Image (spheres, helix red, strand yellow):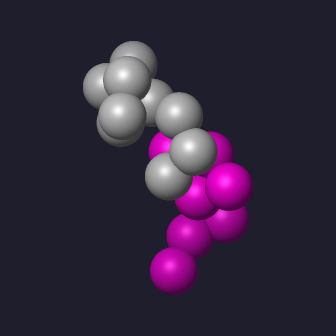
Amino acid sequence: EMRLSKFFRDXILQRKK
């Protein structure tokens, strides 16, 4: 349900930053 999410879901959460 995102666009980034190849993003966040990809790298700012598992890392948290």
Residue 4 in sight here: no
Q: Name the residue nearer the viewer: 9 or 1.
A: 9
Residue 16 in sight here: yes
| Magenta stretch prevailing secondary structure | loop
Task: Establish if 7 lies above or below 12.
Answer: below
Task: Establish if 16 lies above or below 1.
Answer: above
Q: Position of residue 16 (x, y in %)?
A: 31, 25
Measuring 50% from the left and 52% from the top, which residue is drawn there? 9
Task: Establish if 6 lies above or below 2.
Answer: above
Q: Which residues are magenta?
A: 1-8
Whether residue 7 is in magenta: the answer is yes
Measuring 59% from the left and 58% from the top, which residue is drawn there? 5
The answer to whether residue 12 is left or right of residue 13 is: right
Outermost bottom residue? 1
Count of labels shown? 0
The answer to whether residue 4 is left or right of residue 13 is: right
Whether residue 16 is in magenta: the answer is no
